Amino acid sequence: EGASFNLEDSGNFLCTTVAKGDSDFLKRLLSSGMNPNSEDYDHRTPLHVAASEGLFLMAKMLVEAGASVISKDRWGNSPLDEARLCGNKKLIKLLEDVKNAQSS
Amino acid sequence: EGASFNLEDSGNFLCTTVAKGDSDFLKRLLSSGMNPNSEDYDHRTPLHVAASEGLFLMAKMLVEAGASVISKDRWGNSPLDEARLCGNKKLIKLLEDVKNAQSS
Amino acid sequence: EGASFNLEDSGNFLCTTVAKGDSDFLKRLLSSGMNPNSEDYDHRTPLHVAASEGLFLMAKMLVEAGASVISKDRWGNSPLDEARLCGNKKLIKLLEDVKNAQSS
Image (cartoon, rainbow over all chains, first blue to last red; front, side, top):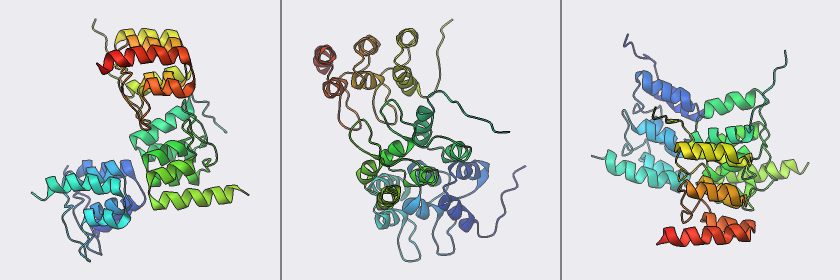
């Protein structure tokens, strides 16, 4: 059909979906067609909150099919910087190489 | 009607599940009455393996199911010790507080 | 007819088979050709699991399957080192011989 989710505050819903850790629900949203680059009310991509309190592979999938690890936040904390704020050195290194790919 | 799981190497199933990162399937399992303290071949409960990966969200869901934090794995690492191993402050204080509450 | 499992969790399926300490199944599927070098969530080959189990017979069968005895794990323990920690001196020497050959 192609009719997208057509959701107001789509960034908010995706960000909360990460917040609820709905791994397969997130993958379902991306597979059905939904850009996880849309920033939330604090101008945070769902990738920002995946970097801060989201899963390794869930964050990596958010990168795929539309996302910006280089996207400065409302405070200038891009997803790599968001992972730094979390202190998630695992996600920090993953976002280092992911950001190296993504900045291009 | 009171159904049961009686599932072959249930601990292996849950350790595999958290390995795959399908948080939703693990949610169905635990909410349906899984065994959050089922040690695998390596004497690791689902909390052990989730903490070892560093998946604080999956480990939090397991804790919501009352996963053990006192029993140790095959390498002398209780889920608290594996939580400290992952180095994620969230899961660390979560499992420390779980230990303190489990004391009672 | 060129049968292949094409199953997920190949190494971890091997780990569950070792977990039940059951030899016939392991031998027949390793003959069928599932990779014994695959590592599970614990980043351990099935040979790692058998070595930590001190299962001399199961371990050597996994060696004939081609599982790496030099490969380390999440804790840095090779099957040789896992057997050393387990205390099966016979298995220690067996894995030492194979590991030295494979190291070469």
